[PDB]
Length: 491
Ligand SMILES: OC[C@@H]1O[C@H](O[C@]2(CO[C@]3(CO[C@]4(CO[C@]5(CO)O[C@H](CO)[C@@H](O)[C@@H]5O)O[C@H](CO)[C@@H](O)[C@@H]4O)O[C@H](CO)[C@@H](O)[C@@H]3O)O[C@H](CO)[C@H](O)[C@H]2O)[C@H](O)[C@H](O)[C@@H]1O
Ligand SMILES: [Ca+2]
Ligand SMILES: [Ca+2]
Image 1 (cartoon, rainbow, N blue to C red):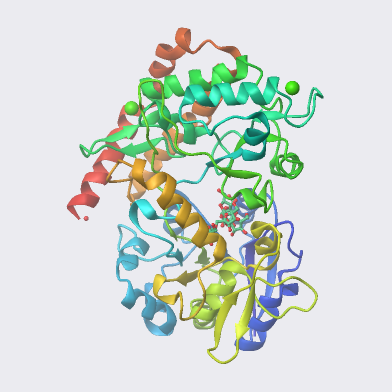
Image 2: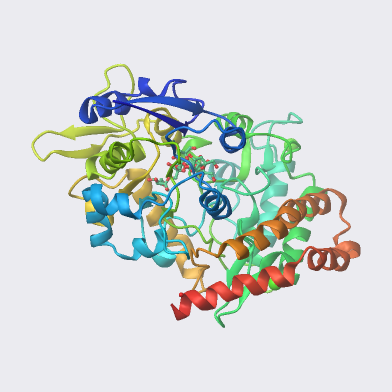
């Protein structure tokens, strides 16, 4: 009758997950009441504290653990293998793995067990994947029009446009009126690393691309990456960068965006930042000084290995597996992922077409897509296959639009035939990689920021590459190359 789940949700959503409409209806459908431990900030740290202290729930919902965490928990018996539960009790999930058997292999550890239940979302394939570019660049076209400027075609054009934004006062002469160039530095949708590809090769959140010769390339020791840093340094020197770029957060970024203070900025979807208007548009791919014109592929995809694990203290495995399988029912997967219908107290993502028993996206009418989604989605394990569109659900309007923009602006310049596959490394290789990344990851962004602020990259570049080798870069690369070769060979 009752299960205790830890979960992760947005701070815009209710403290008690059971106040969400989806979870009220789901309790009626399943007959199971969930008592939630709901962490709405710093989920991973609070989860790790619970595991370390022995305060385990029946299952961790919407978990998102790394592979190294996954295998360590499995080795210590914190979580259990689940392939037998799938086989015995999970017909919805088994049907998905029968329609797309490639996912079975992505769920299976090198020891042959399955330890977690995945998120699956089919939106485009290959270069056309919705994930191929995360930190899209957007520009204020109203300012271009007001100042009599053409859309930049080159990185040199971009400098001149941004200087016009600073010197030409398109939205007022105040010291803080116009922010020519802004970003949230680091990983994710708001970083500036998209532009590094205008110097060839570019960069992504893994700092890892795959050459057309089949050689895995760590991007952050490339001469091309040095030239990218120097370009951003020029913008800094010219007084063109948001003075709080390296300190602000998403809520501040969004507040500045809503006031339309940005000339050029980065985000997944402009509608979350500068709003639903034609004042901002996609910045087309720029040519660099030598004619480099490129879009680096991310290694993102519509799959996450672990959106749920079952702990060793769960005493109702059949009930838990059946609850989880209910999330993989198509109409439930769509709603858990995106929101729901029929709330009279709150805007709805969907309406339910009674006749066809299917879901149809409603217009957002100016509401930010991520804001309403955060309030009403559930997350957790689920599956959305491209066969569902036109049958179970409409394709989201924002998703279709973004797929069209990727195809129009970016795919022609995505010249790497491959990106880096989603591999499942052995526990030994995972722990070697995790020790190297404990040094490398923070160091890479620290130096990048330092160089943008101090201008000393030419003096320090060689020492920096030596430091990366001290931290184990060549071993790191050899391991990534091993698993790439093993993936291509197919074990
Ligand atoms: O790092 C914390 C962790 O991140 C994990 O997921 C998120 C993103 O979750 C969402 C994603 O929502 C979108 C992208 O959604 C898709 C692609 O999957 O893109 C289509 C629209 O173009 C849409 O149909 C597809 O589903 O991202 C933007 C906002 O960035 C949304 O407008 C869009 O829907 O982010 C939303 C807000 O957090 C959440 O409601 C969504 O589920 O990864 C990034 C971080 O790199 C997000 O911060 C994070 O949410 C993980 O799911 C977890 O929940 C934590 O967010
Ligand atoms: Ca000015
Ligand atoms: Ca390299």
